[PDB]
View 1 (cartoon, one colour):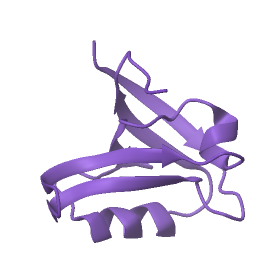
View 2: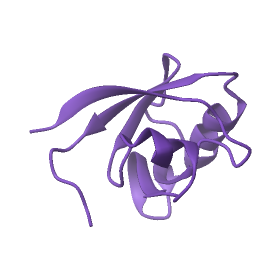
View 3: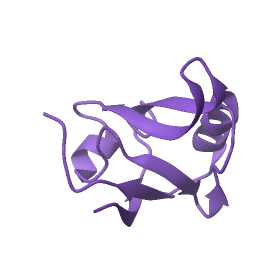
View 4: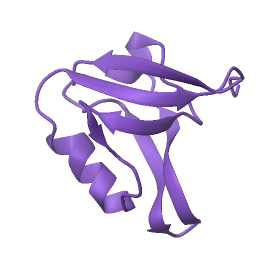
Length: 95
């Protein structure tokens, strides 16, 4: 049961505190942008919502549809202030 969530983070000194994989023309194929790891002690982890496997659909309303890996990183890293991520998330959680 895949659901849409809005997750709001304040950057720490280490950024949003997660990594991404995927992207149009990515080494794995033409993929959406997926959260891979949520780092211990970072903003995404302290917030407690974002998780491995979440697909980042938008960043402060700016769509990631069809973007390359590098495009997604630029949007994620340059977007100013409080960051609201629109994500598509699964019911299941990896452990």
